[PDB]
Image (cartoon, coloured by chain):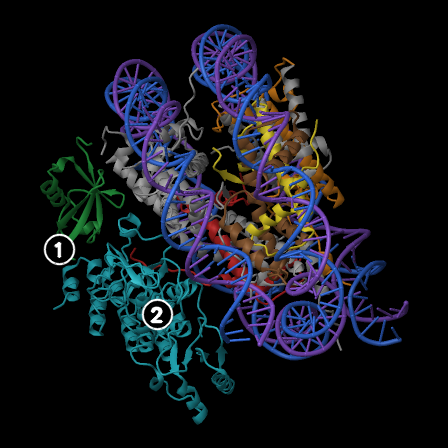
Chain colours: A green, B brown, F cyan, G orange, I yellow, J red, K purple, L blue
Amino acid sequence: HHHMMQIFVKTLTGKTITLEVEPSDTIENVKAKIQDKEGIPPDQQRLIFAGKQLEDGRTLSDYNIQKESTLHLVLRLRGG
Amino acid sequence: KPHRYRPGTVALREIRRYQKSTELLIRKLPFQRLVREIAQDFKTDLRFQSSAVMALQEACEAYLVGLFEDTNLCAIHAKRVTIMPKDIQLARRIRGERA
Amino acid sequence: KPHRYRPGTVALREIRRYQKSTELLIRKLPFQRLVREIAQDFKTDLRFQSSAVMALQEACEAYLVGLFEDTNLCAIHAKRVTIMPKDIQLARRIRGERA
Amino acid sequence: RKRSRKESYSIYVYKVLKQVHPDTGISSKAMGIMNSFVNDIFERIAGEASRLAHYNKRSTITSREIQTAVRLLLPGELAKHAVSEGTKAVTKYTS
Amino acid sequence: RSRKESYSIYVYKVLKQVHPDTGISSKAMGIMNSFVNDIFERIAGEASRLAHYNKRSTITSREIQTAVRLLLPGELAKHAVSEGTKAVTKYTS
Amino acid sequence: AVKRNHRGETLLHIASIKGDIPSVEYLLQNGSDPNVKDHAGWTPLHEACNHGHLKVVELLLQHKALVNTTGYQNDSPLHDAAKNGHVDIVKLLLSYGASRNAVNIFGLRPVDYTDDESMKSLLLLPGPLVLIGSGLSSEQQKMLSELAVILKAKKYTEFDSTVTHVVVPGDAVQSTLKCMLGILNGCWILKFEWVKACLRRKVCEQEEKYEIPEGPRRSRLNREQLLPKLFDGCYFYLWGTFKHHPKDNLIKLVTAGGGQILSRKPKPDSDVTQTINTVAYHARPDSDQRFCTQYIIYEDLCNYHPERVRQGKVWKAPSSWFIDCVMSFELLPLD
Amino acid sequence: SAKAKTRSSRAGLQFPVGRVHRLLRKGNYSERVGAGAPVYLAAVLEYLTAEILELAGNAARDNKKTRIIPRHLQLAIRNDEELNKLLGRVTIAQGGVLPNIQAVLLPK
Amino acid sequence: SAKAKTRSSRAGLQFPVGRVHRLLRKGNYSERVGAGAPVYLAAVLEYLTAEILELAGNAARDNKKTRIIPRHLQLAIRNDEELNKLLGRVTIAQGGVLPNIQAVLLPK
Amino acid sequence: KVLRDNIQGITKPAIRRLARRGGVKRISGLIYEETRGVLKVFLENVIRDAVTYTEHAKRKTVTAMDVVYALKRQGRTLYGFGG
Amino acid sequence: AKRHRKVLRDNIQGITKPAIRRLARRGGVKRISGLIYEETRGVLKVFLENVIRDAVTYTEHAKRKTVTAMDVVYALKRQGRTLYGFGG
DNA sequence: TCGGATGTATATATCTGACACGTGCCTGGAGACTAGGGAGTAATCCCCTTGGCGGTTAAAACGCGGGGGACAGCGCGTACGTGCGTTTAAGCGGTGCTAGAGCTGTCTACGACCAATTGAGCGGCCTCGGCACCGGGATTCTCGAT
DNA sequence: ATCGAGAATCCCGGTGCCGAGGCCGCTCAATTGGTCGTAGACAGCTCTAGCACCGCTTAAACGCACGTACGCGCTGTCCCCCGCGTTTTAACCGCCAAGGGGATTACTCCCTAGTCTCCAGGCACGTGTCAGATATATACATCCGAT
């Protein structure tokens, strides 16, 4: 923690995606990492943590997301 | 001289085997006849689905088992091991059924 | 040697005078403080209508009087006159509050 | 003259089961009990939510009335977890 | 302001019918209002459930009659059914 | 002791909020304890720092007022001073040894509660004797009873809160509920040769010679400074049936130790489990146990050996680890 | 009757048929409400009110008071074997208890 | 997400959001029903179902069975402190009771 | 034609089995009759409700859902027969 | 919150032994053991905690900061403790 | 039985504030009319409830011996009731302040409603493996004799 | 203490059967898209009632001392439940047969919702007076120690 953490993102398909994200990474950077891992464009992605949607401007650490903690990814454009 | 068990061990034997199982403990034809007798006291020439009688038996046996649990607690309170009619009456009185 | 009553007659005197009357038997300021303490454990910076605290006291005293009636029945069952914590526990267990 | 088809939560309960326990099955009587359970809790929560809407002179049952009904009906940790799941589903749906 | 409805005048008219000389206090009238509202809610809820069970969309007077039979104990139910039937026949005729 | 109002505030408290300098001085010279806590946890120092009474703070710190003691939500006096922006109070508290790296339950240092550059740079690194015994035999129990009746002290047979002295027959601390409750609540754990010592000398002689090192010593030191309990900020779920220490034993010991008992199994990938943002105060400063505070306690006899000891925020700990942590008064790491 | 006096008097009641009709319609009980449901419900409510009020007035007279208080309602309800069955899970504010001392506790 | 797949999969659920919505609309609960009420209610129902089914499957494994019967639902509900309180006044058909004997009936 | 004295078909062995499932070790000889009385009351309270539902549906067969509604109406919710 | 938080504690002892004795006398109890009082207090707390928690749950839903008497009446009605005389 | 010491009930003045009644008014209930769909009625189908035998055998009924538990009597000791003097803090009254309940007015976003369409889910087939049953060998409570 | 015989239950393996789990056709209910009217969110203002403090009076709580009545342990008797064997009853199962009445469909009418107009019933407020609360004084019933 505070140098490098490994988090999970759950998709509606039931699969878990493992991301190596900096604690200070922004949600835009996390979306870029998901794009690199899976090819999904960032515009189609919405991230859910603790029953809230994550805004692009605010960073991971200010949302109080620790290591090995699970996010949710939902497609906003052209899902299914 | 044949083998004999002390009074109380077969009772515990039965307690365990009837708490492990889940079947109905009352015979079905006598209970059906009792249900029909009460019903005729209410309305004449009634018919019953078999599921209706089975539901009534489920409910009745669950009620009696719960009441016997409370009765046993009331008997143990009076520092006894035998359940007596006054234990049933105290249980029903406290549950709000007797007043 | 001053006059003295036997143990039990003043108790019956109090039973009669508190069953004739209808006022609240708990002091109001301590009960209000207790209500506010529990409420603060639930939500912070709460305010209470005076009617809310009075309703809570009505309900609490009615509950305690009913529970003591059942407790007395449980004590008399055990062939006693004194009510004991196990009588309260048996009453609450049979009413479905303790399990 | 066609028969009237009756609905049940059998397929949904089976999907949930195959999620939690991918190997175990369920009998017809256990599924009957599970449908009874779902119906019972549905009417409990919906009736409490209806009363909550009537107390506050609201003519709509929204998700916060369902939330308050869940808080009122389920015991502590159950209510906490059920509120968490409902909130995540609602945000997942609206996002 | 806001005006709030109550059953106070009807309860008082009934009281003057049955006991022409006695009065009633404000707290007893509050308890009477609570009682009337409680019984109304009970009977109307049971009638609603009855209509839902039989897939009817109307609460008629026989739903109310069955709810009264289900809720009130024996002689209370008998006399309440008699009173309701008499009122309905007197109203229709 | 001294009577308090319904909020727990001593006369010294009210004087500190009101800033009455002659009142605080007069009370302090009269023997009033400065290290008293109200019902929420605040000391007079907390009230003085939160409002900005420098002179009151100086008099308090003069009279042996602990400066690192934690209040409500484990706030420290420095937390109050920095949060309200009182630079001089911060200077005084640092000059008197208040730690700048302490945290509250949320794991936030005083620096995180402010934004002023200067004070940020300053913050940045530049009683009756109650007796009780544990498994003593007839002669030992009777001799503690005779000591109780000659010292006019209250002796108990079952453990309760107001216990002060706990007597162990052997030299080491017994691994029984009696001694575990004694160490968690900070009671004085005394070897048997202590009690007979008084009977040999007829005097309530010293007890630091009769305190087991590195065991009850840490707990008693921790309580005497009014610091949180051992398991503060930690949640425990007891999984399975237990044989060595029963479920009731473990639950009572957890509750008496400051922890909280969970009723549902802590699924690691659940919002209720993930959103617990508390911090275990008595953990290592940089271990995983600071933020990962939830434990699933299982008995070794059941032998549910996990694939990974920790998954997410939830550890899987044997009951042996729990007992060993209680005996040593320390959060022993599972890795 | 086929009159136009007012629905309450048309039914021969003192309780409001129209108010009961509105309360049924707007209370989320069913999609539709029959014409005779408010009449039946008002008649039943008035009957129950009259029963409790008569018993309470008898209790008030037995205490030689000419005004009903919650104590008299409590006594009326608890002394009738069916009003106590209908209102057995109801606590009445400022009502008190029925005076009974178990025969075991009396002096010998 | 505001998709077009289906409301259940949009919400991430297995239970039917559309059916629950219709049951809320036709159940005589309120005049209107919000768009997020069926989603919340279906999520709560699915969570409770998964709780009971997980506990019941554990109880079925303990009995070395691979198929849940009402006995296992009974055991799961009665052995859980909070599910036994949610379903305190519920009898489960063909479920039996929890085996427990009071300690004073056992031999010395 | 009518039926009578069918409560005696709830025999003493059946009552002892029901007591054993309740955890009862010894049973006084006056329990059985007492138990039968209790049972009758319970049954009369449920059937009377069930029939009342059956008469409202204008049916002449008492269905399982009538019994389920009758039990739920008095705080005895029963899972497994519909509803 | 910048200001301190002040709480109440140990008010269950304001339900004194004479008050519990009066409540027992209205319940018909002639003689009372010395361990009843503490027992009684615990029982009372549980009851209160169940009602207040529901009342506050109603109060939060109306977006209110004051617990009204109707909240208490609803909370009591919710657990089979209908109270007449305070509304509804 | 008997007579003090005491607590409760009965009788009289008298004071107050709460109950009962009158008034303005305004909003909710009532009267009239129209349209549409809910429910009543008739006819039909077929499921499932009732009734009847016949046999087998699981369970109920009856009887008996005996042991263990219920119950009554007795003694002790301790803890609860009763009463008195002291201490606390509840209750009352009054003043003062302000948070927040409660109401009003705009006005926008959300839910109802309607038409079209199409895939989810229900009913029917059916097939194999999970669980029931059985039969033998093994282990473990139980109890009477040392 | 201890072993040893008799029952009871469990463990392991073999056989079979029927119900759970999956497939296929179809139909109807859920979804999509557009429109519209109003519910409720938000801002603002009023004024009520909840909170806080202070001082005085005195009721009620608290602490203690004493004594006795009741809880509780012990013992002894006896009777009534239990365990077990034998006999008898009738439950249960399998089968067949009728037919009543529960579902389902089609048609039709009449009952109820919805809208508009109108006005008096009941609600809020103001005010008089008398029922009930309280003080005061006796009178009688009850309790209990001592006859």
Q: Secondary structure at mark 1?
A: loop
Q: Which residue is at 49% across, 79% downward?
A: F155
| Circle 2 Cα neighbour tier, 10 Å, few/some/many (<14 / 14–19 / ≥20) | some
Q: Position of residue L45 (x, y in %)?
A: 36, 38
Residue that numbered label 1 is attached to:
A4
Residue that numbered label 2 is attached to:
F20
**Is residue F285 visible in the rendered structure shown here?**
yes
Query: Residue B7 occupies which quadrant of the picture?
Result: bottom right
Mark in front: 2 vs 1: 1
Q: Is residue F325 above or below residue G35?
A: below
Q: Position of residue G12 (x, y in %)?
A: 66, 22
Q: Nearer the viewer, residue J75 or L7?
A: L7
Q: Is residue F83 above or below residue L122?
A: below
Q: Nearer the viewer, residue F77 or F202?
A: F202
Distance between mark 2 and mark 1 Cα atoms: 52 Å
Q: Is residue L2 above or below residue K40?
A: below
Query: Residue F21 occupies which quadrant of the picture?
Result: bottom left
| Tally of numbered discs | 2
Q: Position of residue A57 (x, y in %)?
A: 15, 44
In the image, farthest residue toward the bottom: F201
- The answer to whether L120 appears left or right of F266 in the picture is right
Q: Which residue is at 32% across, 67% downward?
A: F320
